[PDB]
Length: 350
Figure 1 (tube, one colour):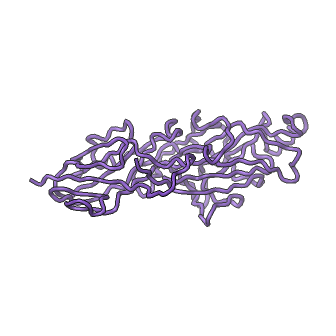
Figure 2 (cartoon, rainbow, N blue to C red):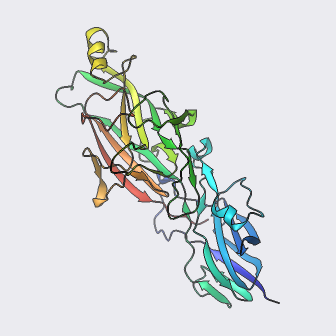
Figure 3 (tube, rainbow, N blue to C red):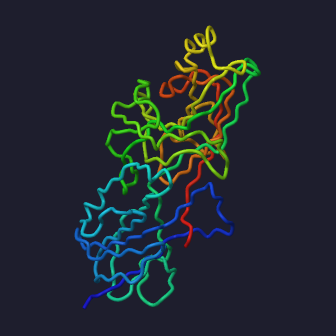
C-alpha cells in the first residue's frame, strides 16, 4: 500500500502571562500544510483558526513539507513546489489592520513512513515522529510604530517653539518581498509612502507611489495603541552608495510664540530647512538604523534593515525644530532622540 498520514502541530507561546494589546502577537486564522512528491502536490489541507493540521493523507517516501498561514485568497491548490517556493506578496491596506499577515516556515525535506507520521507531538502517539518539536512558522511582515512621542524643547527653543503633530507616516516602504528564503528581500525595486513622492531626497527611490493607508491622522501614541505601520523586508545596510531606508515619521506644525510661523520667522525656518511652505516640520526615524541619536535597549545592535517577524517600537523625544525633507540623509542637527525596543513575535494558541 504505502498509504500514510501526517499530522503537524505548530509551536505556540508557552506564556504564563497575558500579552498586552499593543503587542499584536501573531494569530493563525488559516493554516495550510502541503506535502510535495518531487514537484507535484500530493496533499494539501487547511484548518481555520487552528495551530495544527491533522491526518493529512499521503504516501510513504521522501517528500517536501510546506506550511503557510494567513494566506487568505492566495491559490495554493495544485501549485508546484518551485511555484510555491517563488511566491511573493505585496504590502496592503489590510496589513495595516494586522490582517493578511502571512506566516511561513522554510520547506522541509522529510521521509514519510507508511502509516502515521507526526511533527510537533513530542513523541506522543504511536507511529513515526519525524520531528518531536512543534514546528515554528513566522510572520513575513515587521511592524514599525511609535509607543511614545514627547516634546522637550532644548534651551534655545524652550518657551519659544512648540510642535503640533498632525500625521504619522510610513516612508520608503518596500512594496514586495518573497515568502520563503533565508532572507525575504528580493530585487523588485518598487516602494510606497504615505507622504510625498516628490521629496527628491538622498533616500528617495526612483520607483515610488503614495498610498493613503501609509498615513494616519495623529493619535497620541500609547503603549496599548502603538502608532505605526506593517512593512515588508528591505535591506539598506550597504557600506556606502545609495540606500533606501524604511522611515517612520511624524509631521505637524512648528509654532513660535504660540502662533503659526510668519514673516521673518517663517523665512528663517524655511531657509534653515526646518519647515516647508506651510510652516510644517518632519521628524523622521530610520527604522532599525545605526545613528548616534538612536539608542537601542538591552545592547541590541541595529542592522540597517527591516527583518521579518520584528516589532520595532520607537520612543521619540523632540527637542528642537525638525526637517522639511524627511528623505534626506539622517539630519545634521540632532533635534530628536530615539529609544527603540526590538522584539520578535511569537504565535499564541487558540
